[PDB]
């Protein structure tokens, strides 16, 4: 029709002829094309869909129905590829399952759908609910799954994928992370997994963590990774800190005797996810007592106004168990390190003999022997092997394992649901903290808003963070009522005012 | 009458219907008077009540600091000041609502500004968000309670923004400098809007404090901020392939 | 005999700035500096002048002068130190 129009009519009439042409062949038959429009997307007939797309592009009300049809089918396609995921390799599967769906649909939209932005935006809207497959009356495991997937690749592995392999893998991982709707949930979970990868040194490489953090900063601004970047900064400068303290020992008037040279991992308490959850008054050993005071005295020389909080539940080390036929070397945590000094003091030892030795809580004291009885390093001399008030035991000399080095590993690198629920509650506490900020700031602008307008824009303002529950928001008003900050209107509870 | 109020302040509950009718009787008698209908109510009941509650809350405030630090003394003050919003509302004529509340503050927060301002500094530097709100409402009513917490927050932000804009790596100095001040502004605007009611007097302190950290000139040099922000605008408006979509740039 | 060699240790650091306290000397600014705390008879109990700077932190004059030998940076904020008053 254009080729007919080129050779006959004026150029100003080129558009009107073909617009009225589409007005009478695809606008009148718009419902006829809409009939198989659902079918043409479910079957994913590529070349047929493009011809449908080209005609529907010219229609002023022909494209959004096709946009919805693709969105539902991508939603239908995305759900199928995520339901059958195995329980064993779920974090590896879930990211790759989304990328397989996302990769072919980007390949679909860019190639045969002419790369339309609305169709691309349809994929963004459709896949957002796909990755956030929250089962009813449950919690979405996607932020934990992406945390596990990133942590699985970031650990040093027996398979040992190459350094360049992670970077291309992590780049596609960001695309999945762009649709998570729970970025704050991932932040707390990734911070804990970054901790277990940093104190214990269980990381693939130092620069891999920097690359991983920097890619996160490119995805969610700077305030999302500021705590994580502060973790990387402290863990990187800590190498210089130990050398700097080693100069202080040589800078002292008298030589100081202690164990090995310190490998201290001083971290900023403000941004690190580590928290003094245990309140046990764990005393340091007398052999180790002067070791701490020298570093404390040094820290007041090269720093000021600091007053370290001595974390102990993540403090580890070694001990020479000189009681066997040949010397053995074992990595030991400091909770189980101090109780071994009782063995050197006296082979006979009861539970109450450790009470006046470490001054720790009964749960952490139980966990020390529970980490010693299962490894048969010690032998519970009582008739019953369970926990009891007496707990008389000695040193089990029968341990003669062929390994010259073995850690006493507790449940580190595992995820106990108690603290995860606390972390999830902590995330919800952070959710409540930010929700109150938006509420007062919205009231700081107009001072009078209805309930629906106040509710809706907070969803929009916090969309990049999470999806705040309406009941969670309604609690925040009640807190500001209790703190005499917000005031709902007496004439109508819909409206709100200022205190 | 105060003895049944002092006992009411002591934990027990007397007949509030009997009490309220008696106190309302002191003003209902003068209902036929053309001028000063509360004159008999004030000169017979209110002045002895304010004097009695003046000597009791001064006694009570001194009785609390002996076994309580500022972190929990402020909690109990709002506990008493919330009871006073209830106690006088059902025991007195409504025209004496403010003066009993105002005098209650005059013996618990206004007579202990030296103790509060001494512990005001330690609240800000440890960022106790829960206990900072209690200090704000106490010092809001006092005519000279607010202008000290303004200085402490300003000298804390000025001591905090300087920390975040220090020892910057020369690799990405403009982006590090801009995003450091933004998060210090971003965190404290969230902190003021949540905890300190988003008060206007505190935003001026934050604005003035952030002026010092941005214009923190190096010794024997010039302020590097006006050049650094120019280089930050270059680092994102340039034709660069490091992502930086059009929505992200705006 | 059990003997401990390795002590892999982590300690969180925070800020402990109590009001009107010499951050380096770990005492009140109005008192004598820790160098002048010992052998007080040698000192005249006046040279511990309350220093000031653009960092708006107060110490004795013996603190920063001893601190400047090691590094030219203020301890509380990691920026270069100046003198503004006496
Ligand atoms: Zn000093
Ligand atoms: Zn001195
Ligand atoms: Zn300073």
Image (cartoon, rainbow, N blue to C red):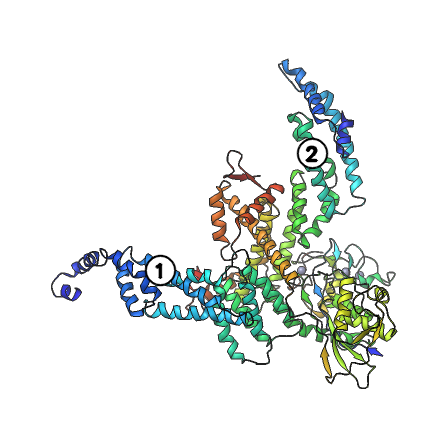
- Residue B240 visible in the snapshot: no
Q: Nearer the viewer, residue B12 or B86?
A: B12
Q: Residue at x 53, y 69 (%)?
A: A214
Residue A107 in which image quadrant: bottom left
The chain under label 2 reads B
Q: Is residue B27 shown above or below A397?
A: above
**Which disc is residue A176 wearing?**
none
The C terminus of chain B, quarter of image: bottom left
**Residue at the image point whose x is 64% and y is 62% from the top:** A417
User: Is residue A162 left or right of B66 when viewed as pictured?
Assistant: left
x and y percent of residue A125 in the render? 42, 59
* Left or right of A203 in this view: C14: right
Residue at x-position 34% and y-position 67%: A43
Nearer the observer, A53 or A88:
A88
- Residue B111, position in %: x, y? 74, 38
The residue wearing badge 2 is B84
- Give residue B142's position: percent from left, percent from top: 67, 38
**What residue is pinned by disc 1?**
A69
Q: Is residue B183 left or right of residue C24?
A: left
Asked if the residue at label 1 sits under 8 Å from ligand 3, the reply is: no
Mark 2, secondary structure of its residue: helix
**In which chain is the residue bearing label 1?**
A
Determine which quarter of the picture holds residue B66: top right
Q: Residue furthest left?
A: A8
Q: Residue furthest front?
A: A383
Q: State the residue at coordinates (69%, 40%).
A: B78
Asked if the residue at tag 2 contacts the one at tag 1, i.e. Cβ–Cβ closer than 8 Å, the answer is no
Which is nearer the eye, A287 or B47? A287
């Amino acid at each position: 029709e254009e080729i007919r129009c080129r050779k006959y009519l004026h150029p100003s009439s080129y558009t009107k002829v073909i617009h009225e042409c589409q007005q009478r062949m695809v606008a009148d038959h718009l419902q006829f094309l809409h009939a198989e429009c659902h079918n043409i997307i479910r079957q994913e007939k590529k070349n047929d869909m493009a011809n449908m797309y080209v005609l529907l592009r010219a229609v002023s009300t022909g494209l959004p129905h096709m946009i919805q049809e693709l969105q539902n089918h991508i939603h239908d396609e995305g759900l199928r590829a995520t339901s059958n995921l195995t329980q064993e390799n779920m974090p590896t599967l879930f990211v790759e399952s989304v990328l397989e769906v996302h990769g072919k649909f980007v390949q679909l939209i860019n190639t045969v759908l002419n790369g339309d932005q609305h169709f691309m935006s349809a994929l963004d809207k459709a896949l957002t609910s796909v990755v956030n497959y929250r089962e009813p009356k449950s919690v979405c495991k996607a932020p934990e799954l992406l945390a596990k997937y990133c942590d699985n690749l970031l650990k040093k592995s027996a398979k040992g994928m190459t350094e360049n392999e992670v970077e291309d893998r992590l780049t596609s991982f960001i695309t999945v992370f762009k649709y998570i709707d729970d970025k704050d949930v991932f932040q707390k979970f990734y911070a804990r997994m970054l901790a277990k990868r940093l104190i214990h040194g269980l990381s693939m490489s130092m620069d891999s963590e920097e690359a991983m953090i920097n890619k996160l900063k490119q995805a969610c601004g700077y305030e999302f990774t500021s705590k994580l970047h502060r973790m990387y900064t402290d863990m990187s400068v800590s190498a210089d800190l130990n050398n700097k303290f080693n100069n202080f020992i040589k800078n002292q008037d008298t030589v100081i005797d202690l164990g090995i040279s310190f490998q201290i991992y001083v971290l900023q308490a403000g941004a690190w996810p580590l928290t003094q959850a245990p309140s046990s008054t764990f005393a340091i050993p007398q052999e180790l007592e002067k070791s701490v005071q020298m570093f404390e005295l040094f820290y007041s020389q090269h720093f000021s106004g600091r007053k370290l909080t001595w974390l102990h539940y993540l403090c580890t080390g070694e001990v020479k168990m000189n009681y066997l036929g040949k010397p053995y070397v074992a990595m030991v945590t400091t909770y189980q390190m101090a109780v071994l000094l009782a063995f050197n003091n006296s082979e006979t030892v009861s539970y109450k003999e450790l009470q006046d030795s470490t001054q720790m809580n009964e749960k952490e004291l139980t966990k020390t022997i529970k980490s010693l009885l299962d490894v048969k390093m010690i032998n519970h001399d009582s008739e019953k092997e369970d926990i009891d008030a007496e707990s008389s035991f000695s040193l089990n000399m029968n341990f003669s394992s062929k390994r010259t080095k073995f850690k006493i590993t507790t449940s580190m690198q595992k995820d106990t649901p108690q603290e995860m629920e606390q972390t999830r509650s902590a995330v919800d506490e952070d959710r409540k903290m930010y929700l109150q900020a938006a509420i007062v700031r919205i009231m700081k602008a107009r001072k009078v808003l209805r309930h629906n307008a106040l509710i809706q824009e907070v969803i929009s303002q916090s969309r990049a963070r999470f999806n705040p529950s309406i009941s969670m928001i309604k609690k925040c008003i009640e807190v500001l009522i209790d703190k005499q900050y917000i005031e709902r209107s007496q004439a109508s509870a819909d409206e709100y005012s200022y205190v | 009458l105060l003895r049944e109020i002092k006992n009411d302040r002591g934990g027990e509950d007397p007949n509030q219907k009997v009490i309220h009718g008696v106190i309302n009787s002191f003003v209902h008698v003068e209902q036929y008077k053309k001028k000063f209908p509360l004159k008999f109510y004030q000169e017979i009941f209110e002045s002895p009540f304010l004097t009695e509650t003046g000597e009791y809350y001064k006694q009570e405030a001194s009785n609390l600091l002996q076994e309580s630090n500022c972190s929990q003394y402020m909690e109990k003050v709002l506990g008493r000041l919330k009871d006073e919003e209830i106690r006088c509302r059902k025991y007195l004529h409504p025209s004496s609502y403010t003066k009993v509340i105002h005098e209650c503050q005059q013996r618990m927060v206004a007579d202990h500004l030296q103790f509060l301002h001494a512990e005001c500094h330690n609240i800000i530097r440890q960022e106790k968000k829960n206990d900072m709100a209690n200090m704000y409402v106490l010092l809001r009513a006092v005519s000279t309670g607010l202008p000290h917490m303004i200085q402490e927050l300003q000298n804390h932000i000025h001591d905090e923004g300087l920390r975040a804009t220090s020892n910057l790596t020369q690799e990405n100095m403009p982006t590090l400098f801009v995003e450091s001040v933004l998060e210090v502004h971003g965190k404290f605007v969230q902190l003021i809007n949540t905890v300190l009611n988003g008060d206007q007097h505190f935003m001026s302190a934050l604005d003035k404090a952030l002026t010092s950290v941005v214009n923190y000139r190096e010794p024997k040099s010039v302020c590097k901020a006006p050049e650094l922000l120019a280089k930050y605008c270059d680092n994102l408006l340039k034709k660069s392939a490091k992502g930086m979509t059009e929505n992200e740039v705006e | 005999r059990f003997e401990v060699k390795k002590w892999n240790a982590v300690a969180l650091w925070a800020w402990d700035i109590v009001v009107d306290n010499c951050a380096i000397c770990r005492n009140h600014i109005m008192d004598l500096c820790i160098e002048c705390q010992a052998n007080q008879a040698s000192a005249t109990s006046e040279e511990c002048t309350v220093a000031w700077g653009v960092c708006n932190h107060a110490f004795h004059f013996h603190c920063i002068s001893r601190w400047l030998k090691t590094r030219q940076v203020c301890p509380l904020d990691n920026r270069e130190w100046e003198f503004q008053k006496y």
